[PDB]
Image (tube, rainbow, N blue to C red; front, side, top):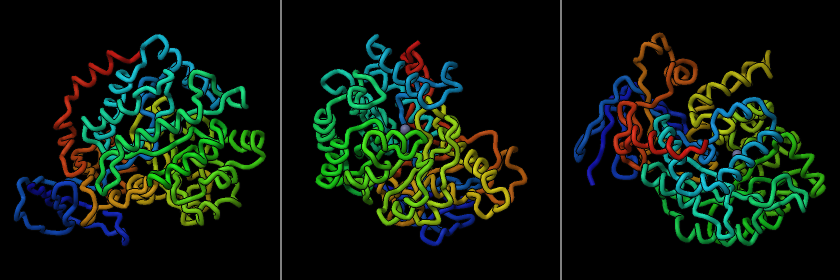
Length: 456
Ligand SMILES: [Zn+2]
């Protein structure tokens, strides 16, 4: 029950309510939580002191949108340069194919998940929300059991978002039958997951969320069902939102915009975070704000697929919560959240060539990647370095030869570097990464084991 002191961090970014930062300052940790953050903290009941000099410390990064199983689908030549339709076909085909060859069972997803999750820790990411949409077998298989098992073995904080594709081509869908589950099978399964896995209490390490793939891909019955289940069991709701084709598909199936559809079917609530949000009607943005939905900025796939730049400034101006994420590795293709912030930092600028004040700043992006994401996930106990909050902490060295000359360390973190490898990472008060290495997980063994299971 003994504490941990991180002493003399060169810079500490808190993202508390004042955006306080401190210099040559400490973080005191006791079990799952932060006890204090400030200069010259007492080592009174401390059983280990960690030398933070030369480091910048942030709240642990929170990846608010992953698809772990896609770790197996990286850097496929056929999928290097493809639009959404071909990409979606390519991933679905591969996952369905590997699955009926017996090459993609929950045992495989578990080890893919273990690799990408460990990569995540090493990149300073302390919480991941994975959306798994793939459940063939008639009895919905243990894919989420498998990702939760990897997360738990690793000690990374975890949100399991049970996804689906419930709208088939026989109803106007762009999927297939092997992945199309009846709505009731999705709903039954979700209930069992909550009861078995959900840790609603503060500092909870595993939580469940309900996440249809999207309005073009799922039945309204599912959304309404989930809206009921979310209020009955106090869990959260997640889906994709305003991908370029969606407005057209939503109007064709239902005669309304994707937002108006969500509104109708119970999803205009503070009960919701929404992935991408690339091309909304501007007129709807103030409505996102009053509804209290949050939005996850996913720059890497938005660029990768040719979709472009989501109006993040507008969301910020409207007071909408904005978080950040990588998405799956079939459309990123890495799980490197920190690197992806540099992508956003730069790619937004050409869209407002003469109004640099509109450009997202390093600190606004770092906020998205911590506090913003914590809020997307409904976690007031994460995303902030201050007393009472979770001791989830990520730190990077500032004294490498590739960061010589850096005047502001936080900007430096986005704008410079050969490597996004974190030095020191703490989750739920447990040191998981030190000197850029895992201290509990066996790195080489995990690389070997997962590599052996990746399908040809
Ligand atoms: Zn996604």
